[PDB]
């Protein structure tokens, strides 16, 4: 098997070596600049609290695996996990409600937990002052990891299986040839490698600079304190680091706790962000590294801890009879979105990262990376973890510093899924931005782009809107980052004509004599048709899982325009193109360009769309002029445009593409032409609702690499007759009707109880699914939610969706919910 | 020699066949759908007035050649030119002044002419009512072409030399293979061809559609009338089409006149534009074509001619004793800028156009095209004539129709060189457009782009501007499309810091493993240097003439960004790239993309530029961080930018490039940072003045293909040591010091008399040059003008520049006029 | 209906505006209305100040109800009024002129 070098013998690197060995890959060298008995990164100071419940399905699964693995890691009859359970307490009504949402995540991801009353919290955790406790969330399987001991036991058993460990060894560079890694440089020479995995914790950006790779983590310090012996605890636990009570979270005050024998450990995020410059740490001679003297531990700053100490005495009055004994400011990593950084670098073939990982998720990350290296894919969806998810404006040192510090400040806060940052904003705008502001756009941001969710100009329409379109009142949570204006925008899209800004949707151009060949292998479509065809298609992995859904337009013999999901797609096509070019003939070369920022797109949709465009173009937009799922060049308002006939919202009209410099003119021409037809600008809230009424699947939510096309209901997009394409072999024999789990459309029976995503779905009282996409459907006048369900659940069956602890009745409904016969789209 | 097919036996196609034959190419077939004795296009109805004087040097030269050639074309002792001279009369003070400007063009281009008083006009042209005549311009060498007779004499002498003519033969299509022309399709089969030249007059767009080429001409009708016999003319001229008086222009009323024996001919542009749909004309059976029945002649509309008839009786009262005899509405071609359409198509190798050409310029166009075909270059600058000059928004049917109709309406109007159209406008805008409007930009347009010439916000600075910067009053003409605000913008660029919008400047990306190879052959620079270098360089033709000046930045091994002059450059690189790819190996492929519309550029210039940028970037902008004429990637205001250190205006700072979606953020970040330094936005008027103070050459004005680098003073940009590049052989042995004519900087001695361009330059009373670029120099506090001068004229010599008939004294001055030691640019 | 005390109507709006209205919109005003007048409650431009605001000025999280028609931006505007200089639009406050020999 390939020769592997892992940089870092922390909890990540040692678990990765272990997960590779179990899969029969043992030609591995693990390097650490610190001594092997105590390397001195963040693993060497972590207290090891493991709370499994998380809003992310992937992170919850990583944590469940870590608990399982650490319980299994044992020597002398003592494992590396003390399963004391975990308790999160609420001191405010806001937090109490959020614990009910978290109980929902627990059920969705298969973690057992219970909501506790104030009395039950007091029974479980007698040291609590129960007066301010409003309730708690108890998860019996949470507990305390012995991370440093796990590293030592992993080193022992992988060394026995053939892995080489070299401590006291500092990587100073990375050797490469031909765009692929060949070795790792140290003061003593080059260690050869076919594969290198950087598991370097908060030194990850320093390693990345060695190959010109931007690694978007920020080293930050976090306070952890131990008390003197607590009188109330005398004689209760094993010395010196025993624990019997559940690990304790006090998120309203940014604090967590564990026992250390008769002392308490206190972790605080309730201090200013503390960015650290790794180049100032100094090199530690390995002989000097000890418990209180290691690169990851900075001097304690007591002044930052005083408020946390006061809040601790309020929660746990027994601690007022102890004192602070020792504290430190410990360094670890934060990222712009709180997710880890996994996968193959853009810059160098065979060079991978696995960085910004809590002890809590460490074994799950290692397993996923071992699967990726040994088979070419992870068994768990890595869409939120892949290093290639970031846009270029999100990789600057300034962006990474500002947003990662904000992620630290907000780490334990209750936040709505649509909550925007207030800074940095306005990084990327479409050519229509000034017009959008004239119309009172309400902007939210994603990937750096400012995106209108609705337009205040449209509030003036509500007083003439027919009553059937008016939705009921929303509760406070589903009402956040929502407006009744969205109903009016849906109404006018369905009955008049609307202009949507589609500029931010990822746009790739694939060009060259090898473009068709590349796309024929990567996608599930037969794209070898005369130019002008627009095809919806999938990208699979070799196991048949769905990596992405894409729209391909063939604009000429050697040029294709792709509508994609994000920069994971960009990086995937870039590497595939480079490999085909490198290994191919003079006729196989192909280039991939992300053209999003240089171009723009208006979705012109609604039954009056032909009436509008006819005023500003002499091109033929009738059915004979441009058929469904076709593209052609036209002129509108004097501007050259590529028109594509398709609609996410399910109405007559076209996506209209042009260069950025022409966008404002195109906008203004269509706007003026639309005045007699009541044209409006329409935003993302209406867009999302109308598209869900059409049954569109959103990659990352409604399907991931965990699902095959047939489970997702996307069988129509796979041409099994093709001679060859990635994933074909895995899909042989599979059908929608035989799939054990199938994506289903649910509608909420009461017409009012809107759900948002991730809520667990129950069939005859058993958890069998969870909400993927959701929105209020303005045309069907009820809330909509999608979920995978067992294949034996049928259209017409009833399921319950749990929202803030309340069960909402919903019906499995045939989709599309609107115009399934496509009458609005044809002719 | 190659097999040539010419489409059209009008005055253009027959002169082209003749010019090819004289150069030893006689394997030519000329096709016309009409009968050879009277083909029936516009040549078959033209009255043949030839006025040589024109604002364009190239068009004047084409007309002078036509007069020479038509005088030489003779049979039976009668030539095809009746050299009666030409008279333009003025009835307004505006027109009288414009005739003095036109007398300047005449002197500049080597045409003899004189201004005449009202009395002299009456002596020359006794039929004038002298009361309203204010003066005239008399050019003795102008006169009347016999265009139909010339066609017949050219057919006769080229047929003798081996050319095949096929009348009654309609081209229905064009045959091609491998991207090159192979033949011409007719109802009777394919006529083979290595080269095809479309000389199809107003059917040019119909021919172009046969190969998918946009040919930006519009067929329009123009009235021409003949009177009954005029009593005052009885017995004076030879019948039936004799003429003795000069041809007569009456431009204030959009009229022209000639004699036809004792009758008058009247041409009128004083009617509504009359667009013609060529597809409605009907096919004329060749046997039916006659003087009054031919595709080019539409029914006369008397109602449109009544005002012209009244104005005619006022000018020439003798005509009130005649009547209208016959009129017609005759079809010919107009284009968006009034220039012809010459050169090789973008779409098809070996397919050329020579269309939208007046009889007046016909022989000159034919000569230039014969030179192009037989040697690879024209001996006359075709920059204003090349079909590839147009931007994509300028090729739409809507743009061509609107602007060509406006060109018809304005054909005989007095217009300032900076006069903008009022529509269509706002086609292309940069990402800074809304900010520019906040600052009160005054926009003019070129290539479809809106470009600020100054900002009204800056008027507030004039009251604190030091007196040395305040220019004198301008006269009305030089004051048009000018403001004193430009002085303030120059002042602040020289003393503080300014932000220029460089977005519209043509930006090409040349990429692929063959990119370096392509550019090494096409340019005069050795570009094989490690990435990061910015090089100013020239593109030559094989005769060593300057096709373009370009700035090349090597951004990586296989990617170069070029700053170019326009779409002639784009098309030149596109074809050269395709040819290298087609004939090359797997390592020779190269792509060319025009990235202008997808990107943007701020020129951040002035002595405070480092102070400003240091507030919004952590990158090193010191001399050690980024040296002169180098590029590197940086982050400014959170935006990824490519910074290049150079300055057209001659100050510290950089061109800052980014994608369009990031432009507004980059703008706003720099704007906010610049507040304590007094940053301003600065427009094109100041830009042009400051750049001329640095001695920058503007391609198309200061040098064309008529000049070699040494004549232009650009010898420093030619690396003669290179092994190979287009034009090297022609340049062997040439130097600046030995050049017979050299580009010189002149400053106007009185400090106030601003000149604009094209004014003739005199040395010891002889015309020896003409003004190329000109501007008021705000730093040197005097008007500046460039001109080629004989090599024997030296720095310090005095010359006169004629402006509206007045001689202005100027001094040959060493350049750059500002900071020739580059102190402001270094360190 | 259940309604928050600051809940605005969505129509009719923009009946009465001060002379500073266009400048306020340039600065991202969040407007509520009273007596027909559009009144900025905070300015989105000021969100850029939060990252340099001293920690003593940062308020705790708000619950959903008290968080309606509220922003953390208001803390920054208070901070700058107390430490720098601020421009408040007082145009809507009722202004009467009482004139004549009997006014006093
Ligand atoms: C600091 C901290 C972290 C922490 C915590 C409390 C504090 C104060 N409490 C936690 C908790 O209770 N529960 C939990 O799940 N995590 C908690 N953490 C975070 C946790 O400690 C870290 O996320 C985790 O330990 C990171 O592990 P990882 O294996 O990724 O990283 P590492 O231990 O830092 O190891 C990296 C190794 O790389 C070596 N290195 C770096 N550069 C080089 C070079 N150039 N050459 C050779 N070796 C290199 C380092 O020496 C290090 O050992
Ligand atoms: C209409 C007009 C033009 C004009 C003028 C007065 C009127 C009323 N007065 C002029 C003046 O005094 N001085 C001057 O310099 N020009 C004046 N003009 C303009 C002039 O007539 C035209 O610009 C010039 O004649 C154009 O010449 P050109 O040789 O370019 O064009 P043409 O005569 O129209 O010939 C084109 C031939 O192409 C043939 N054709 C077209 N399509 C086909 C196909 N498909 N197959 C075969 N042959 C084709 C036509 O039959 C035509 O003969
Ligand atoms: Na916090
Ligand atoms: Na006119």
Image (tube, coloured by chain):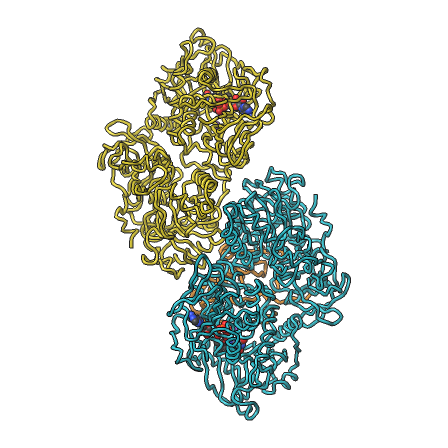
Chain colours: A cyan, B yellow, C orange
Q: Is residue A652 left or right of residue A641?
A: right
Q: Is residue B298 above or below residue B454?
A: above
| Residue B42 % position (x, y) | 51, 21
Q: Is residue A755 left or right of residue A309?
A: right
Residue situated in front as seen by the camera: A810 or B315: A810
Q: Is residue A720 left or right of residue B634?
A: right
**Residue in the image at 65% along x and 62% along y:** A707
| Residue A538 % position (x, y) | 62, 55
Q: Residue furthest bottom?
A: A235
| Residue A23 % position (x, y) | 57, 69
Q: Is residue A297 above or below residue B343?
A: below
Q: Is residue B357 above or below residue B594?
A: above
Q: Quadrant of residue B614?
A: bottom left
Q: Quadrant of the C terminus of chain A?
A: top right
Residue situated in front as seen by the camera: A317 or B504: B504
Q: Residue furthest right?
A: A796
Q: Residue furthest top?
A: B235
Q: Quadrant of residue B86?
A: top left
Count of picture labels:
0
Q: Is residue A624 visible?
A: yes
Q: Is residue A622 above or below residue A383?
A: above
Q: Is residue B633 left or right of residue B400?
A: left
| Residue C100 % position (x, y) | 50, 58
Q: Is residue B475 visible?
A: no
Residue situated in front as seen by the camera: B459 or A328: A328
**Residue in the image at 40% along x and 44% along y:** B519
Residue situated in front as seen by the camera: C20 or B101: B101
């Amino acid at each position: 098997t390939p020769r592997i070098v892992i940089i870092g013998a922390g909890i990540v690197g040692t678990n990765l070596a272990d997960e590779l060995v179990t899969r029969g890959w043992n030609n591995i060298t693990v390097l650490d600049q610190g001594p092997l008995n105590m390397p001195g990164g963040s693993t060497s100071h972590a207290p090891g609290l493991v709370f499994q419940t998380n809003p992310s399905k992937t992170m919850a699964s990583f944590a469940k695996y870590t608990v399982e693995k650490l319980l299994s890691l044992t020597e002398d009859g003592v494992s590396c996990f003390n399963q004391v359970g975990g308790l999160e307490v609420a001191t405010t009504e806001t937090r109490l409600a959020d614990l009910k949402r978290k109980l929902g995540y627990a059920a969705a991801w298969g973690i057992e937990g219970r909501l506790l009353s104030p009395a039950e919290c007091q029974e479980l955790y007698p040291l609590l002052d129960g007066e301010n406790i409003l309730g708690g969330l108890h998860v019996p399987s949470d507990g305390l990891a012995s991370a440093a001991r796990a590293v030592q036991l992993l080193i022992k058993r992988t060394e026995s299986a053939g892995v080489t460990y070299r401590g006291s060894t500092t990587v100073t560079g990375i050797e490469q040839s031909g765009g692929r890694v060949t070795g790792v440089q140290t003061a003593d020479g080059v260690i050869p490698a076919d594969i290198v995995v950087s598991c370097a914790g908060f030194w990850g950006a320093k390693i990345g600079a060695m190959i010109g790779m931007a690694v978007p983590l920020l080293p930050l310090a976090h306070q952890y304190v131990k008390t003197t012996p607590v009188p109330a605890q005398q004689g209760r636990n094993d010395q010196p680091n025993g624990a019997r009570l559940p690990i304790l979270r006090h998120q309203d005050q940014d604090l967590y706790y564990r026992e250390h024998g008769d002392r308490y450990g206190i972790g605080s995020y309730a201090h200013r962000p503390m960015p650290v410059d790794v180049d100032t740490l100094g090199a530690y001679a390995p002989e000097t590294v000890s418990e209180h003297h290691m690169p990851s531990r900075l001097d304690f700053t007591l002044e930052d801890f005083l408020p946390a100490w006061e809040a601790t005495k309020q929660l746990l009055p027994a601690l007022a009879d102890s004192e602070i004994e020792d504290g430190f400011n410990g360094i670890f990593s934060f990222t712009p979105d709180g997710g880890p950084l996994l996968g193959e670098s853009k810059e160098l073939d065979g060079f991978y990262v696995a960085e910004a990982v809590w002890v809590t998720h460490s074994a799950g990350v290692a397993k996923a990376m071992a699967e990726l290296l040994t088979t070419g894919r992870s068994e768990t969806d890595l869409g939120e973890c892949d290093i290639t998810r970031f846009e270029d404006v999100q990789l600057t040192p300034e962006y990474v510093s500002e947003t990662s510090q904000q992620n630290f400040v907000e780490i334990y806060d209750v936040l709505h899924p649509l909550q925007p940052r207030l800074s940095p904003r306005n990084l990327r705008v479409s050519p229509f931005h000034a017009r959008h502001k004239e119309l009172g756009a309400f902007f939210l941001e994603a990937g750096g782009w400012e995106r209108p969710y609705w337009f205040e100009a449209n509030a003036a329409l509500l007083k003439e809107m027919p009553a059937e379109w008016l939705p009921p009142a929303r509760d406070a949570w589903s009402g956040m980052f929502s407006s009744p204006i969205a109903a009016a925008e849906a109404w006018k899209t369905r009955t008049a004509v609307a202009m949507y800004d589609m500029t931010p949707l990822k746009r790739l151009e694939v060009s060259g004599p090898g473009a068709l060949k590349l796309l024929q292998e990567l996608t599930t479509a037969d794209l070898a048709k005369k130019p002008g065809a627009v095809t919806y298609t999938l990208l699979l992995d070799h196991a048949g899982g769905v990596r992405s859904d894409i729209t391909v337009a063939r604009l000429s013999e050697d040029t294709f325009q792709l509508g994609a999901n994000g920069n994971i797609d960009t990086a995937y096509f870039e590497r595939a193109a480079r490999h085909q070019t490198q290994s191919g003939s003079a006729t196989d070369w192909v280039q991939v360009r992300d053209t999003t920022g240089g171009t723009c797109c208006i979705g012109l949709w609604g039954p009056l769309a032909r009436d509008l465009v006819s005023k500003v173009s002499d091109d033929d937009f009738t059915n004979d002029g441009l058929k469904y799922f076709r593209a052609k060049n036209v002129v509108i308002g004097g501007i050259p445009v590529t028109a594509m006939r398709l609609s996410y919202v399910g109405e007559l009209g076209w996506e209209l593409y042009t260069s950025a410099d022409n966008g404002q003119r195109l906008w203004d021409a269509l706007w003026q032409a639309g005045q007699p037809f009541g044209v409006i600008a329409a935003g993302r809230a209406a867009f999302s609702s109308l598209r869900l009424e059409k049954g569109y699947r959103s990659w990352g939510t409604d399907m991931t690499t965990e699902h095959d096309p047939f489970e997702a209901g996307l069988g129509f997009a796979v041409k099994m007759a093709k001679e060859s394409f990635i994933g074909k072999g895995a899909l042989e024999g599979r059908t929608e009707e035989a799939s054990a789990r199938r994506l289903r459309c649910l509608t909420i029976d009461d017409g009012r109880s809107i759900v948002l995503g991730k809520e667990p779905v129950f069939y005859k009282e058993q958890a069998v699914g969870y909400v993927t996409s959701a929105a209020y459907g303005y045309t069907v006048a009820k809330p909509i939610a999608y979920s995978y369900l067992p294949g034996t659940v049928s259209v017409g069956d009833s399921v319950d969706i749990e929202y803030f602890g309340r069960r909402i009745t919903a019906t499995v409904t045939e989709d599309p919910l609107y115009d399934p016969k496509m009458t609005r789209l044809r002719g």
